Image (cartoon, rainbow, N blue to C red):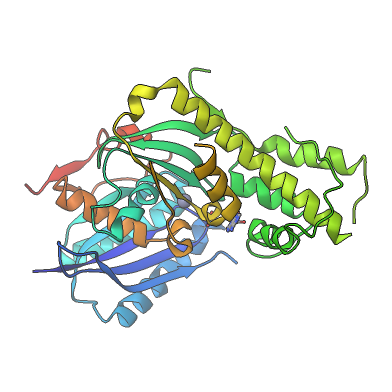
Length: 344
Ligand SMILES: Nc1ncnc2c1ncn2[C@@H]1O[C@H](COP(=O)(O)O)[C@@H](O)[C@H]1O
Ligand SMILES: [Zn+2]
């Protein structure tokens, strides 16, 4: 009366494998195993570590002969990295004679806040703001298969920009932007507010490439290291970056009011979404808000597994064993591409 899912994420630099326990359809699934091997070349890393990782996962999950579904990121991303997990997933599927689902990567980010409350919250339609180190997108979700991008970044992601500006202040570490928030919060009022920093179609867009450039052209009028000044500058940096996002979100909500007539829930996921100041400006300068945890907003295979559970039960669809990776996969063309198949 229940089943288990083997999930593989291989679109990014980190290799991710998970085992989910869908013990009941009237309850949120549980995680039996969730591993990430960080790249610390892209196609080789997955190719060399996808094997030992899953083996380790099946041992820890204690269910090598109990998984009933294989979910793997089909795209988008680099063909070399995607293949490493996709070809491997097929091997698992053929050996176990079990169904396979080629999952869209962005679909995982959008659907993962539902998993906690099964499929209840949030409900369609809902809007989502994916703000990570690789994504900066605003998406409308009308259905499990109907997703529309309303605003996407042009150059880099917000996380990529904040880190780049964080290393110029300069902070170090795995996640630089997260560290930059701390030094500015320790002196949230204790920082000397003396510096007045200077920061800056047929489809609305984000942009973050100029923030590092504008940052360099302001430290050139001052000096490059007073913590009362450091915490002050860092505040104005993240503020203006968040200002750009809120401004573009406003433009979207004002341009297409008909799109947003029946949505009452805003989802902000991605690594950057853990930023309290960002969370605050969203709720202030804009209808519920949902903030997914940190261990799910970052790239992982759990969201891939849950996404597969979504499409297997709701759409009753499955992927053919001949599916190839997709470099550029438009979210609106989710079911347009070969080759989906029904179990219904
Ligand atoms: N609390 C935070 N505030 C701002 N940025 C963050 C925070 N936590 C993580 N990040 C950034 O999010 C990115 C990683 O998220 P992800 O790409 O989802 O793995 C990195 O650029 C981090 O610096
Ligand atoms: Zn991602």
